[PDB]
Image (spheres, coloured by chain):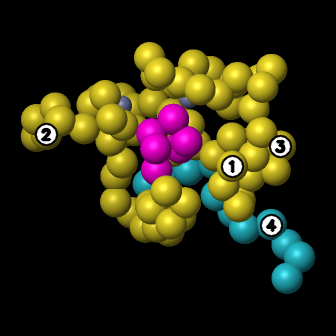
Chain colours: A cyan, B yellow
Amino acid sequence: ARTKQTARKAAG
Amino acid sequence: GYWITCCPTCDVDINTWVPFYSTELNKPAMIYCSHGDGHWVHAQCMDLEERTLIHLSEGSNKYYCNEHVQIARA
Ligand SMILES: [Zn+2]
Ligand SMILES: [Zn+2]
């Protein structure tokens, strides 16, 4: 399904 | 399209919103409902747990909002 703001932000 | 009133019980408001999912910072996570031509809704307004939301985002399965999910599909 199409989504928005489901990407994990960097800082790991 | 982030600050729309996605459904009759929509809780997201540009004047009060704060992050809930681990993937949110300054904007609400959203998912597309495939009913008819389709429409965007806020994931939180659908009571979707984070893992369910992430799984939906990582696959090709279509999502149907709580308002249209029981409608006979085709
Ligand atoms: Zn909403
Ligand atoms: Zn819908």
Q: Is residue B47 left or right of residue B26?
A: left
Kind of residue at badge 2: Arg
| Residue B33 seen in render | yes
Kind of residue at badge 3: Asn
> Does the residue at mark 3 contact the one at mark 4 (Cβ under 8 Å)?
no
Report which residue position mark 3 lands on: B26
Look at the image and give the residue range highlighted in magenta: B43-48
Q: The disc numbered 2 marks a residue on which chain?
A: B
Q: Are marks 3 and 4 on the same chain?
A: no
Q: Is residue B54 above or below residue B13?
A: below
Q: Magenta stretch: residue B45 in it?
A: yes
Q: The disc numbered 3 marks a residue on which chain?
A: B
Q: Which mark is residue B73?
A: 2
Kind of residue at badge 1: Phe
Report which residue position mark 4 lands on: A9
Report which residue position mark 1 lands on: B20
Q: Residue at x 74, y 52 (%)?
A: B24
Judged by depth in the image, the label closer to the viewer, 2 or 3, is 3
Q: Earlier in the sequence, mark 2 or mark 3?
A: 3
> Does the residue at mark 4 contact the one at mark 1 (Cβ under 8 Å)?
no
Q: Helix, strand, or loop for circle 4?
A: loop
- Residue nearest the observer in this picture, B15 or A2: B15
Q: Is residue B72 left or right of residue B15?
A: left
